[PDB]
Length: 352
Ligand SMILES: O=c1ccn([C@@H]2O[C@H](COP(=O)(O)OP(=O)(O)O[C@H]3O[C@H](CO)[C@@H](O)[C@H](O)[C@H]3O)[C@@H](O)[C@H]2O)c(=O)[nH]1
Ligand SMILES: [Mn+2]
Ligand SMILES: [Mn+2]
Image (tube, rainbow, N blue to C red):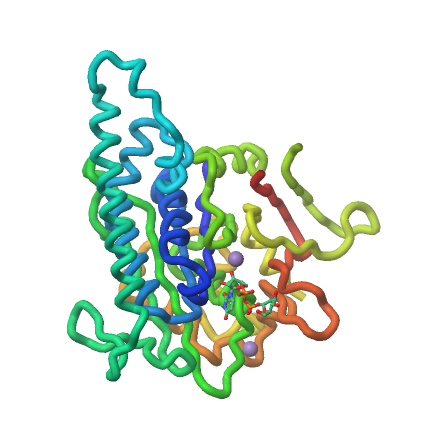
């Protein structure tokens, strides 16, 4: 069967990470061949850049058109920039097909999307003096890049509006963890640990996958292929049920980008606020088949998700020490990946 997957993308700087490339990665995720309620996309923005927030907003709106198109016509790859680069053979058709008509309209929609993103980048090139202001009229909470509250915004999903055929889309979650002078943030490693916790509060999928912001999914069946291995030339795979044992794999395994791996392996254990002072998160670590308690409102969940990204959350905890992505510059050569402990079940499937 098909287990839920939480997909993590970390970004920091739209000037080094062009918004359109990130958008293409996100669109290839949102259009993946998978039940929409069982794939979720979390984008961490450590730059707290309004440009990234707004380009992700525009991206979700375009996804509402792009996703049903790809699924109707079995498009590959589902990153529009790369799909539209491939040449099509119009001469083999006597008359314009429904596919060709739909594709010509989709391509101009994509060109228009691109122009809007270019406009966002241009406007970002030069500050106004009072900092940025949002749709509302209210100021952008991340104007001070090193001194700003935690921000979470859920797009699409169950309550985020339908695609062009009237169907729900996967959740897309913007996350910018809190930053305050006097608190270390540990860069990507700290972002990934924050995303482990945010995802656990909001979806808590048994499997996690971390993609670079330019690593678009090339084959929409990638998650199904992974599940063919994870549930009872070639790519990297690992399976282990560890007990006791001078036998078998000894010690932890570390996993980086592009691999689906099982979440509970992160929680590998030696109280329980080695995990930090979140009742909701600690409870989530105890559900062996994932999910969230049915009686939590998106509103209370958004509480809890904000709490788990506060800048002091990891103080007095094992995060970055023995749990999650591990902090370094001492002995441990990680923060090249998540630490999967021996204790129980471990499984990894990496994409080609
Ligand atoms: O605060 C941050 C910084 C980076 N990243 C992510 O981590 C990855 C690394 O990108 P990079 O531009 O290399 O970030 P750096 O913090 O600068 O990490 C580098 O810092 C040195 C100087 O840039 C480099 O020589 C090293 O390759 C590397 O450790 C990207 O996916 C980034 O989105 C975050 O999530 N949060
Ligand atoms: Mn810390
Ligand atoms: Mn990355």
